[PDB]
Amino acid sequence: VSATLLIIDDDEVVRESLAAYLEDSNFKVLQALNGLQGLQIFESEQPDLVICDLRMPQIDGLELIRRIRQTASETPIIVLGVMSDAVEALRLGAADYLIKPLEDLAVLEHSVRRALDRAYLRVENQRYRDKLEAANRELQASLNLLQEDQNAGRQVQMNMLPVTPWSIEGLEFSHRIISGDFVDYFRVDERRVAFYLADVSGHGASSAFVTVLLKFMTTRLLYESRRNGTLPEFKPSEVLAHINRGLINTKLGKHVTMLGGVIDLEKNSLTYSIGGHLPLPVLFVEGQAGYLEGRPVGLFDDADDRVMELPPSFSLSLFSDGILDTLKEKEASLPEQVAAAGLDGLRQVFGLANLAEDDIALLVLS
Amino acid sequence: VSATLLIIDDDEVVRESLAAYLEDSNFKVLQALNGLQGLQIFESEQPDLVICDLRMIDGLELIRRIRQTASETPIIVLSGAGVSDAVEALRLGAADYLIKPLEDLAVLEHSVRRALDRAYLRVENQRYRDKLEAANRELQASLNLLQEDQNAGRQVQMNMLPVTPWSIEGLEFSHRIIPSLYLSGDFVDYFRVDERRVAFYLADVSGHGASSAFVTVLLKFMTTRLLYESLPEFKPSEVLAHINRGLINTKLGKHVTMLGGVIDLEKNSLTYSIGGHLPVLFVEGQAGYLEGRGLPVGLFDDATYDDRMELPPSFSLSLFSDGILDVGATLKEKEASLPEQVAAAGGTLDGLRQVFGLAEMPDDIALLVLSR
């Protein structure tokens, strides 16, 4: 099972020898006693290669080599006439010319394979241009498909955000994001205000597809309690737990860390609980920013609480995994000093001016 | 600039001649003194094609040296001698052989472009097999990402979907979704309000895709956010107006159809306003279809939504989301004459429509059933 050939020589003796040798090399041999019929055979079916010896009167000679090139059928053609006919062959479009009589049978083989190689080379090479084009025109199509997804995901992501600046009885809230990260704060029983800064791992629509569920996690818990609720006092530590076990329940493949805190206004007391891995929160009293003690992945299923009294005037704020200030060791000791330098107005001044681009999101609680 | 050819011809007069001819035909001619000149030059320059006279120039040995450097550079042999010699050269990969004085001007240039082409093809395709492989690797990776993104797409609905079958004071709600692997836009949700009013609705996002999934989440984010905004409290017909102006504000460009219905259990009545409906009550007797004064898709900024019936003891409603099953072709309206009979056979039971269900779908199907 190999490339088929077509021999056209007047000599039945010579045509007899070459055919056996070629067919012995797995090359299907088509024998053409007379030049004319060798042309008809090509019309019905197209062999991979055509060998022939220019002779007269039976053999067409140049007439044959012309027609094949004019019939839009391009196949290698080896000719076996002297220079006058050999030189022309190459001009008309012949692969190569071989002398007679050749005693070494192999010499014809090599010249035969060069033609096949440089023929199959043009067929495949031209196919790569069509297949590759077909690939990119199917890839760039799904790329623009992803872009429409990135945009769609961002729109619904910006919609879940709280109103800015929304302030309740002297408590101004301001969040600026520039996107898996999300920050929301909705009042509870009026007296208790809850806020958080979720920082979903990863990026893209999938990441923003986790944050959309997150709000559903938190919103539902409040909704789950029928006004009175299961309990009288809302608990931050258990809130992060519901979210936790829920992210395992559903194979999102993303771990989320968020700083949740409920501020009771009647008792002026704040109960918060660090999700696990975030740039520490910055409290702002006496003009000197102070870090708040905080502690995992938030993605475990095992069967803490930070309570603090608050002054009338304070400033508290969160970051979404954004370090621009010398890593880890000093990347946590420098932030505290910078925050007091200027809240929303100061950080804002520092923010931007970088084309580099997890996205950065900050919440200001004044 | 077309190509960089290297000629190694001992004969000054002749070599200069070839230089002028080739140079004119948009070529750079590098004249090599002798066999070694070309060899020392070749290593640094790496020309596209080398043409040298077979006189003794090292001759065949030079070709052997070029084959050793693993270069694919073609080699045209000029053996003007009327002799066994030329063939051995081609044996080493030499392109062709021209017999001097080779007065013929055209032939030489004919054998030159050939080799440069049969080489440019071997380079172009070898570069095509690399870009193609890189394209497929990058393509299949994005599909794997999309698949993973689609998996996360249908897994988010698990928490949002209501419990089935959830029944309150005699009313049984049941919904079963049959996804065709690919995400669908249809999303159904029913919720209780004031414990004295019950609302149910079926939505469907145009076509299918990841974007559609994002639209299904904002619907539950809209229908519920208007709930805690303020015993019939308000009317869905007015609600569809609010949800409409919200969707057109997002600029998503996704078309959503909804089948709303609020029930007052104290008075046993139903107020339904269906936007993209195009509402079947079993009645226990002859199957009846609900009438909606306004059936607008929701795309037009202007809201022309209107609502409209005391519920019977043995109630029996159903909502289908763009689910079309032949029976001739019976498309559209023809399809719509046939289903009333089928629902009756199904006896308004989610289960009986379920048994006919199942058994490749363009869009996943989601239905809601009410039993009383």
Image (tube, coloured by chain):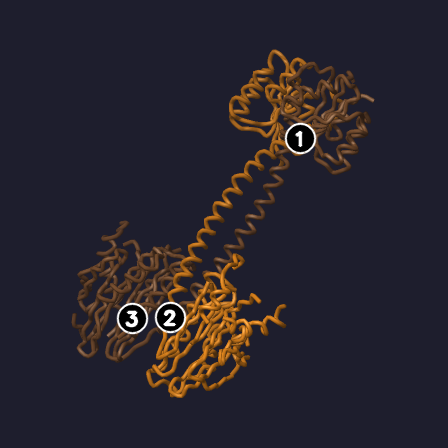
Chain colours: A orange, B brown
Q: Is residue B210 above or below residue A12?
A: below
Crowding around mark 2 (Cα neighbors within 10 Å: few <14, some 14 to 19, many 20+) is few
Amino acid on which the number 2 mark rests in the picture:
Pro
Q: Quadrant of the C terminus of chain A?
A: bottom left
Q: Is residue B9 above or below residue A144?
A: above
User: What residue is shown at x 56% (from left), y 16% (from top)?
Assistant: A63
The answer to whether the residue labelled 3 contacts the one labelled 2, judged by CB atoms less than 8 Å apart, is: no
Q: Which residue has dot 2 on it?
A: A165
**Residue B28: x percent and y percent?**
67, 27
User: What residue is shown at x 69% (from left), y 14% (from top)?
Assistant: B103
Amino acid on which the number 3 mark rests in the picture:
Leu
Is residue B300 at all visible to an observer of this figure?
Answer: yes
The answer to whether the residue labelled 3 contacts the one labelled 1, judged by CB atoms less than 8 Å apart, is: no
- Tag 2's secondary structure? loop
Q: Which residue has dot 1 on it?
A: A114
What chain does mark 1 sit on? A
What chain does mark 3 sit on? B
Q: Is residue B186 left or right of residue B76?
A: left
Q: Quadrant of residue A344?
A: bottom left
Q: Which residue has dot 3 on it?
A: B226
